Structures are given as structure tokens and as C-alpha cells.
Image (cartoon, rainbow over all chains, first blue to last red):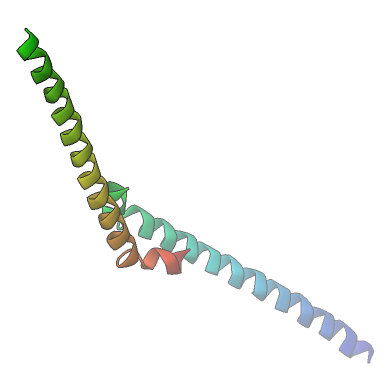
Length: 49
Length: 49
């Protein structure tokens, strides 16, 4: 049981780290995509407005 | 001069009528264009946001 406790602790730690890294990468991709979609296309909307 | 007076009155009248009609046409066109340009295109921005 003592050996299992620290292993479960490390498991939770690495799970949290993986979650954080995943969220960070997804955020980077979403930001780049929104910027590139707002700067390049959707221009007739500007002249219409 | 009395004949010129009513002429200038009718001149201002037809001028303001033409101006109103032009503004109305331009407004209708701009509204239709904005609606048709927002409803159809600019959809990738929605998924980006």
C-alpha cells in the first residue's frame, strides 16, 4: 500500500501536466487560426459595413 | 421676378425630392448587400471564434 500511494500521486501529477500541455497547444492553434482567418479573408464585410 | 420666385421654389422642392429618393435607394442597396454578405459568406470566422 505504501508503494501504491506514491505511484498514484505521481500518476495524478503527470495527468495534470499532460492536461495543461494539451490545453496550451490547443490554445496556440486556436489563436493562430482566428488571427489568420480574421486578417486574410472576410473583407467584403468591411466594405459593406 | 415674380415669375422667377415660384420657379426657384419648385427648384428647391424637386432638389430635395431627388435627394430623398437617392438616399432611400442607397440605403436599400446597402442593407440588402450587408445582409446577403453576412448570411452567406464569413463562416470560418464562426468556427474560429
